[PDB]
Image (tube, rainbow, N blue to C red; front, side):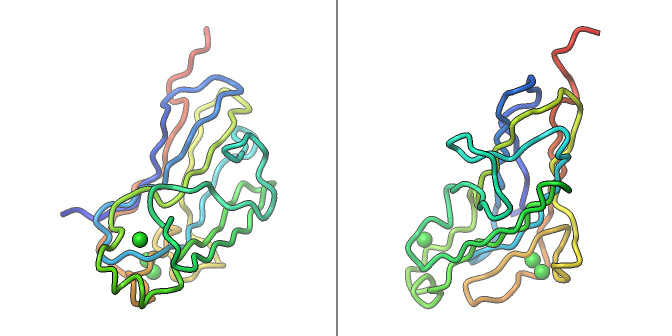
Length: 171
Ligand SMILES: [Cl-]
Ligand SMILES: [Cl-]
Ligand SMILES: [Cl-]
């Protein structure tokens, strides 16, 4: 019965050069159809890379998750500031009439994945953040329902995800 979006890492600790996979997971978001998210990371410490290993550019979209994967004319766009460590992206179904008719809303799952290469062994956070670009954000998140309306209330935003609180580093 708790509704949430969370940044979930596959690793708590990661050595230099390792990949840390950040899964953006929703739970119990009624009639979910899409989102706009604004993620922040420290670009001295982590570098976003595709599932093929290639560095994100200013336009690279996060990787696919386990939901938002159906042929409802998905619209995906990203704008990333790699110097500041900001990933702003939107992923949403457009063919909403058809999605509603299928009557099987994607309320729980991984909306997207962002992989990060560890540049430096330092405790660091992957967060969602409010931004002047997204006046409707709730802690950097905008969730949509299958009528195309924002889901304006009733969910937690569980973030930041922290890597390397503990480190394998002799000291
Ligand atoms: Cl679907
Ligand atoms: Cl909102
Ligand atoms: Cl929202």
